[PDB]
Structures are given as C-alpha cells and as structure tokens.
Image (cartoon, rainbow, N blue to C red; front, side, top):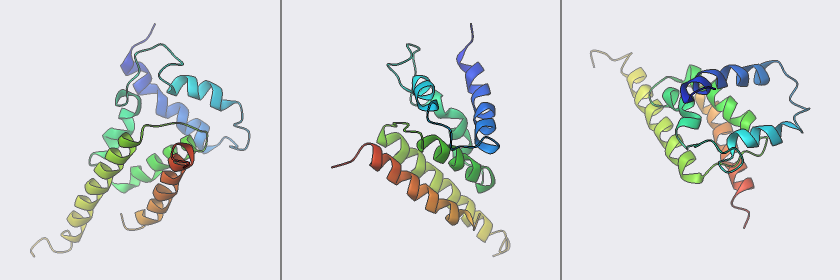
Length: 141
C-alpha cells in the first residue's frame, strides 16, 4: 500500500513519541515487532542498510550537534532493545559524523577569528557507550 518515502517520512515521529514521554521500563515486548521492522529476513520487503537509517544520515552529513544529540539519543534508545547492526555501517557513519562535526567545530573556532557544539563531547560519552552495546551484541569473544 505504501512506498519507501512514506515510512522514511513517518518513522522518526513514531520514534520521538516512543522516546520522549513513554516510560521505557516496559519495552519487553517491543523487541519482537521492532526486530521484524529492522531485520532483513524477518520482513520480506527489500530492506537496505542506507534507506533504513537515511533520515538519521541526512542529519549526520553536516547538520550541527543540536540535532545530533537527539539523533544519538534515538540510536541509544534503539540499541537498548537488542537491535543488531552490521559494524561497518556504524563505523563509517560515526566517522562521517565526527569529521563533519570536527569541520563544524573548526568553523566555530574561525567564527571568533573570521578576519584571522562543545558540550557534545558529553554526548560522545554516550556515543562510545553505545559502541559498547554492539560489542555487547556482536563481539563477545
């Protein structure tokens, strides 16, 4: 009944609703439905590693840390429910994010020196912590 752009447009609204004001201590049953959304062989739609998380990726390739903090909050609230990702996607996507925000931080350092964001490292703790989740899922020995 629907297309790829449909669920690409309507997934983060549902995810902010389940993130922000839902008590996240009763998500024991969500890892069945959410995995059938997010596993390739569970739902027989032609799923991909780019179109599935592309709405996050459009904010990773040059949008600032104001929206990236809540983006990594969705990745955090998503990983706490056993969401299995391939590792090279996370490594490449986090590398693109850190070089984009490093270029933006160099742009901020030249905003006080045009003639000649910073609390996001507190969110980078959670970025590192999240990385440990996929090690806790995939690389267990």
